[PDB]
Image (cartoon, rainbow over all chains, first blue to last red; front, side, top):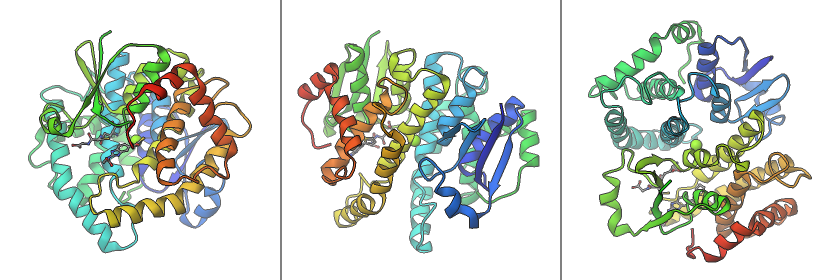
Length: 198
Length: 198
Ligand SMILES: COC(=O)Nc1nc2ccc(C(=O)c3cccs3)cc2[nH]1
Ligand SMILES: N[C@@H](CCC(=O)N[C@@H](CS)C(=O)NCC(=O)O)C(=O)O
Ligand SMILES: [Mg+2]
């Protein structure tokens, strides 16, 4: 069908969907809105958030709902129902952490202490948990790449913006990042995508 | 299989899983820990968070991952692939909002202010969106109950504790909570569960 993704000009919460479409070699309109048009566009949305994915003018919302929809019956899904549960669980564990950040914070000091707090104390613990979880396997779940690996590469890319040294002690999480980045369709997208901070 | 759910003595993030087992008429061990015992259990969990659900000796984590797993191939999941997406989206929409609250905040003057801002400035927008979303239909998605309906009733029960007037302008939302609460297996669980604030 006809796919149109609407988001800001950032990776943010649309990037997992952009990776999936890249990987499945599915063409879509990557619509990136002007911030000035935001109040308008927002009053057409089911819940006032983006991203939304229009599928033949049937609207889907909630980036991970959409991601799960798109990967259903693909090799990105997890190879069994329980492995699908582990893929969902890892994704939510990463999302829970990312959602802790006051991304829409006003007081640029209060923001920067919340950030410093989360990055100084919370992120290292998560990195260590993820490194133990991964251990010596190739991918986070099962014997092949799933969208949870994509989500790790996406989340950690943003986290490295604010904390460059995040993985100095975790070469195996770096390896996994570079393996996702090396999958040809993902590599092409990374090279083609707009360069944005977030 | 043999199921063991581990959580605090609280509805909280385990409640959605408890509703699903009640509705599907599935026996499980409802293991409620007290605080004394939490640090020692924590250190054995790969992500240090509960709920967990042990299934024939394998551990699953992340409450919505687990709920989605348990409902796969039941009437609770949604019928079409698109309806499954909408179920996941509504669940995520409710959960994202439940996530803004500083549940852990120990300085209660800052806690109480935050709760109040959220409940006054934010919540009513979401209620309005959910009510418009529901329209005149019996259930959120499709024409039969799904776990999104259960998560609505659960999330709103907790919200109503802090903002008792939350649904005063939303009779269609109150009707939906009452329908979920009238489903006999759910009714019986609500009657019998331990009474806890949250
Ligand atoms: C003294 O206990 C707490 O404040 N902690 C606490 N932890 C909690 C975790 C979850 C919830 C809760 O009601 C939901 C969150 C998402 C859906 S229901 C409420 C909670 N309250
Ligand atoms: N998104 C997760 C939240 C898990 C979570 O943060 N659980 C809390 C209590 S609801 C917890 O284990 N906190 C205790 C701790 O972190 O030590 C889920 O739904 O399972
Ligand atoms: Mg979430």
